[PDB]
Length: 24
Length: 163
Length: 184
Image 1 (tube, chains in turn orange, blue, yellow):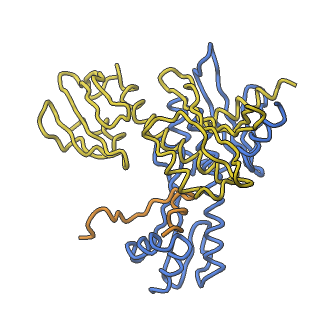
Image 2 (cartoon, helix red, strand yellow):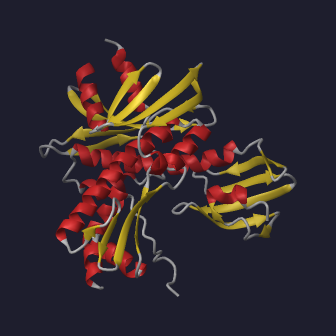
Image 3 (cartoon, helix red, strand yellow):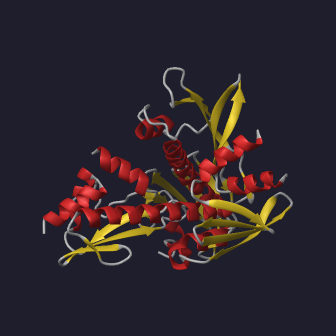
């Protein structure tokens, strides 16, 4: 996912969903 | 060497301009103006005042912190980074709208039938680097994973296909 | 014609700036990273990253030297942005702001618990007893109580806390919201 990695940098992107936690 | 140092500083600022007018420092970008006044007794800052001609609400959180802390560093960087991200949002929103059935619903919102995707920049104080938050009125988890897999542009577009 | 220095110093207030460095008839590119100290109301001395022209390819900058703290993943930032292939001015600024963003995060963390020194909180005086270089382990006194916290560097979240040596959960959460959790 190279595109997402670059977008995270450019946009300082923070996803609403935290995939480090369970989705119950 | 004078002229080469300006070259590197022009690169540093890119499309932003800095000007020393009186005891103020003006940050300009196409009619936008952020004025920074600082009082420097001895070799330290004792007070600071900020004035904006636009984005007063969008910048209130970080600008409020900087004034409450006299931190001109966080203040000027926040404006610079804000102007940058806002332009990135416009470009990204435009690319998605033009490349897909998504249509421009507002300054920061795109729509596809009843689906709404909104782009947000918010201040994670005390950081002067705003964070991008992309929200939807349907299934946030599917959108976020698609953005995680394919990036912002393709993630949003592919997400519209799931509706 | 001395307004230039005044103009530059104004630009430098932003915290990130490029500048040329001439050495051995080679023009190095310097990245200046300056942090404002809210306690001293002064700017700390700049950190530096120095780039040297490649002798192998045209238009390629290489990492030559730096003095950033060891908690900054400078080489991971450089590789992720440039791939040792595209070192455009745009990418260098992207690399510079990425290092500066990490510096500010640590700096702000340490400054937070030092600004509380002397201040009164919950009608109790705050005193800082210990803090590591990254501000991830902190011990402070509030009135007659001793609070010890462990912080996650990634999300600035207090993940472990002890109140007078006893496990605590009422103070967990974002690091900068701890001042509003003492009412519990």
